[PDB]
Image: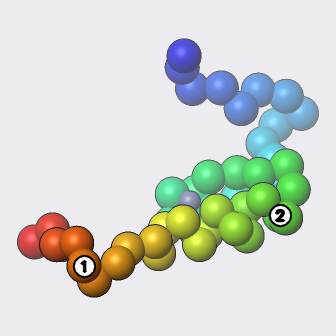
Amino acid sequence: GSSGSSGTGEKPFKCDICGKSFCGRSRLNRHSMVHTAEKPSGPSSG
Ligand SMILES: [Zn+2]
């Protein structure tokens, strides 16, 4: 496995946290939520 994303350039969408692309926002939108998936119960990183 290596850097791909080959085909008619990149996707019509892109992330803001990791820049992840998604052929369809319907997916990306949700992905942008995984970046803020952290509970208080667990510790944090300095
Ligand atoms: Zn992302």
The amino acid sitting under disc 1 is: Ser
Nearer-the-camera pick, 11 or 30: 30
Determine the residue positioned at 28% across, 83% down: 40
Q: Quadrant of the N terminus?
A: top right
Nearer-the-camera pick, 3 or 33: 33
Callout 2 environment at 10 Å: few (<14), some (14 to 19), or many (20+)? some
> Which corner quadrant of the image does residue 44 belong to?
bottom left
* Mark 2: secondary structure: helix
Q: Quadrant of the C terminus?
A: bottom left
- Left or right: where 35 falls relative to 15: left
Question: Label 2: which residue?
Answer: 25
Please give the count of numbered marks on the rendered protein: 2
Location of residue 32 with respect to 18 vertically, above or below: below
Question: Label 1: which residue?
Answer: 41
- Left or right: where 20 falls relative to 27: left
Determine the residue positioned at 62% across, 52% down: 20
Location of residue 17 with respect to 20 vertically, above or below: below
Location of residue 2 with respect to 35 vertically, above or below: above
> Which corner quadrant of the image does residue 12 belong to?
bottom right
Badge 2 residue CB within 8 Å of ligand 1: no
Residue furthest top in the image: 1
Residue 9 drawn at (x, y percent): 82, 37
Residue furthest bottom in the image: 40
Residue 35 drawn at (x, y percent): 49, 68
- Left or right: where 37 falls relative to 41: right
* Mark 1: secondary structure: loop
- Left or right: where 26 falls relative to 28: right
Callout 1 environment at 10 Å: few (<14), some (14 to 19), or many (20+)? few
Residue 28 drawn at (x, y percent): 73, 61
- How far apart in space, not on screen, are marks 1 and 2 (Cα)? 31 Å
The amino acid sitting under disc 2 is: Arg
